[PDB]
Amino acid sequence: RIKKISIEGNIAAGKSTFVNILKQLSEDWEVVPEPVARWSNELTMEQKNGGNVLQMMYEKPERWSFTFQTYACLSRIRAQLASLNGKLKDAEKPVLFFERSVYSDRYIFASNLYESESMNETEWTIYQDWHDWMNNQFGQSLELDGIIYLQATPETCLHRIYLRGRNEEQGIPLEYLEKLHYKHESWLLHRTLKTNFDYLQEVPILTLDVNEDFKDKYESLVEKVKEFLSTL
Amino acid sequence: TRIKKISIEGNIAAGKSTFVNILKQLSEDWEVVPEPVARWSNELTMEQKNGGNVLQMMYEKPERWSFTFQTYACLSRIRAQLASLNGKLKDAEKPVLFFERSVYSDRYIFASNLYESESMNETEWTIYQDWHDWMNNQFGQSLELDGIIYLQATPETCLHRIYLRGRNEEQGIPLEYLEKLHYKHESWLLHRTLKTNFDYLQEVPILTLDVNEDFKDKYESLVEKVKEFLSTL
Ligand SMILES: COc1ccc(-c2nc(CSc3nc(N)cc(N)n3)cs2)cc1OCCF
Ligand SMILES: COc1ccc(-c2nc(CSc3nc(N)cc(N)n3)cs2)cc1OCCF
Ligand SMILES: COc1ccc(-c2nc(CSc3nc(N)cc(N)n3)cs2)cc1OCCF
Ligand SMILES: COc1ccc(-c2nc(CSc3nc(N)cc(N)n3)cs2)cc1OCCF
Ligand SMILES: O=c1ccn([C@@H]2O[C@H](COP(=O)(O)OP(=O)(O)O)[C@@H](O)[C@H]2O)c(=O)[nH]1
Ligand SMILES: O=c1ccn([C@@H]2O[C@H](COP(=O)(O)OP(=O)(O)O)[C@@H](O)[C@H]2O)c(=O)[nH]1
C-alpha cells in the first residue's frame, strides 16, 4: 500500500534538493535517489561499474550509450525494489518518492541518445524490447501512483549546473538542455508522448515551477505536494 | 514440478539440433526449445531482425558487439523457455522439455570465452555477470534444470561436421576456437571443475553421450540411455 511517486525534470532542476527536503518532513516519507547520481562520485561494485561507464560515455557516447542505458535501468529497478520490499516499514501513510523513473530512462535519456545518433536502430530496438521485458517480468510493483514534474527553464538549469560547481558537468550545452526540456514538456505537460505503458497515459501529474529559488522558501511547494497526495 | 526441464549441451555442430529433432518425434510428452541464436541464422519478427543484425556485426567486429549480442541472446533464450513452460505439455503424464543449450552456456561457455579473447573488456564482462546473476535470481526454481545431457564430440568431429553442414559464415570457424570451447565443456560437464554462481548446479544430474559416431539412422542406444536417465529425475 506504499504510494509510489516519481520526481521528474531536467538536469539541475533541483530534484535532489527537493527530495532531500521531503524525506525530512515526515517519518512516513522516504527517498530513492537514482543510480546515475550515485555513480557520479569501501564503495560497491555497482559504483565500480557505474564509475567506468559514465566516464566511457563521455569519451564515446556512440560506443557506450546502449551498455550504459541498459545498466542504469537495471540499477534503478533493483534500488526501487530494495526500498519497496524493505524500508518505510510499516508506516501508517507510506510514500516512496523516486528520483526519476524507468520511463525517464527510456523516454528522456535513451530516446535522446538514439536521436543524436549515439545508438543505432538495432541498439534502440533491442533496448526498447529489453526495457518492455525487464519491467514486465520484474518491475510490475513499480507502477507509479503519481508524478511530480519540477519545471525549470533550460536557462535556470545551466545556471544551476554552474551553481553546483562540479568540474565534469561544466561543458554541458544549452541546446542539450533544450532537447531534454522539450522532451519533458511533451511527455509531462502536453502529454503528446505515447508510451508503451498505457496506465501512464492517465497517471496524475503535479507540475511545480522551481525557476525561483526554493531552498529557503519551499512551503508553498510542500503544500501542493500534500494536496496532490490526498487527491490520489 | 511438474514439467521436467533438461538442457542439451555440446560444442558447435556436435549434433544437438539433429538429436532434438530425433527425440521430439518419439513421445508427445516430449518437447524441444530451439536456441534463439541458431534461429537468428538462416516480414520477419522484431527479435529475428535484431538477432541477424546483431549476429553479422558480432562476426564483423566482436570486440564492439560481444556485450550487446550476449545480453540479447540470453534475454531471448529466457523468453523462449518461459513461453514453452506456458504454451506446452499442459496435460500430459510425464512432460519433458528439452532446451537446446541453456542460460549457463550463454555465460560460462560463450560470453566467458569472449571475455577471455578480449572481445569484452572487464567492465562489460562484470556488467554482464551482474545482470545474469540478478535476473536468474528472480526466477529461482522455475527455469532451473532437472538434468543436463552433454553431447561430447572432439573438435575434429565438430570441424568435419561444420564442413558437412556447409554454412558460409561457418567455414571460417577455426579449429583452435573449437578446441577452447571443448575445454570449457569438459571442465563444466565432464571433470566438473568449473566454479559457478548458482548453488544447485553442483548437484544437477548430467548424462554424457559420446556422439563422435554418426547417429542419424542409428540412434536407439543413445535414446535408451536418455530414457534411463529420465527415470531417475
Ligand atoms: C551534446 O553535448 C553534451 C551532451 C551531454 C553532456 C553531458 N555531460 C554530463 C556530465 S557526465 C558526469 N560525469 C561525472 N564523473 C560526474 C558528473 N557529475 N557528471 C551529463 S550530460 C555533455 C555534452 O557536451 C560535453 C562534451 F564534452
Ligand atoms: C559528448 O556527448 C555526450 C557526452 C556525455 C553524455 C552523457 N550523458 C549522460 C547522462 S545519461 C543518463 N541516463 C539515464 N537513464 C539517467 C541519467 N541520469 N543519465 C552522462 S554522460 C551524453 C552525450 O551526448 C548526448 C547527445 F545529445
Ligand atoms: C577467432 O575466429 C573466429 C572464432 C569464431 C567464429 C565464429 N563464427 C561463428 C558463426 S558466424 C554466423 N553468422 C551468421 N549470420 C549465421 C551463422 N549461422 N553463423 C560462430 S563462432 C568465427 C571466427 O572467425 C571469423 C572468420 F575467421
Ligand atoms: C571474428 O571473431 C569472432 C567472430 C564471430 C564470433 C561469433 N560467435 C557467435 C556465437 S556466440 C554464442 N553466444 C551465445 N550466448 C549462444 C550461442 N549459441 N552462441 C556468432 S559469431 C566469435 C568470434 O570470436 C573472436 C574470438 F573469441
Ligand atoms: O531552489 C534551488 C534548487 C537548486 N539549487 C542548486 O542548484 C543545483 C542543482 O540542484 P540539484 O542538484 O538538486 O538538481 P538535480 O540535478 O538533482 O535536479 C544545486 O547546486 C542546488 O543546490 C538552488 O540553488 N536553488
Ligand atoms: O549423427 C549425426 C549428427 C549430425 N550430423 C551433421 O553434422 C552437422 C551438425 O549437426 P547439428 O546441426 O545437429 O549440430 P548442432 O549445432 O545443433 O550441435 C549437421 O549438418 C548434421 O547433418 C551428422 O552427419 N551425423
Image (cartoon, coloured by chain):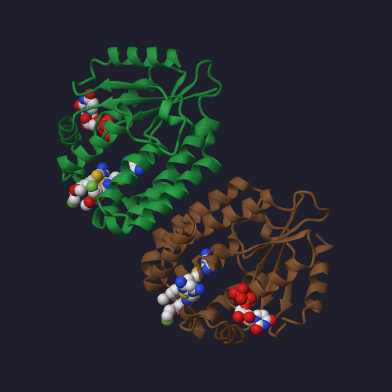
Chain colours: A green, B brown
Q: Is residue B191 above or below residue B196?
A: below
The residue closer to the viewer here, A25 or B43, is: B43
Where on the picture, by quarter, is residue A52? Answer: bottom left
Q: Is residue A176 above or below residue A100?
A: below
Residue extending farthest front: B43
Ligand 5 falls in quadrant: top left
Q: Residue at x 52, y 55 (%)?
A: B75
The percent position of residue B31, horizontal first and vertical second, equals: 72, 60
* Residue A82: % across, % down: 51, 36
Q: Position of residue B117 (x, y in %)?
A: 43, 73
Residue B227 figure quarter: bottom right
Q: Could you tell whether B8 is left or right of A47 in the image?
A: right
Badge count: 0
The residue depicted at 37 percent of the width and 52 percent of the height is: A124
Q: Is residue A185 above or below residue A49?
A: above
In the depicted structure, whether residue A60 falls above or below residue A20: below
Quadrant where the image shows the C terminus of chain B: bottom right
Residue A22 visible in the shown view: yes
A43, A168: nearer the viewer: A168
| In-front residue for pair A103/A51 | A103
Find residue B4 and report its image quarter.
bottom right
Q: Residue at x 25, y 50 (%)?
A: A116
Q: Is residue B189 left or right of residue A121?
A: right
Residue plotted at (22% across, 40% down): A179
Q: Is residue A41 visible?
A: no
Q: Percent from the top left, x then y, of residue A155?
A: 15, 32
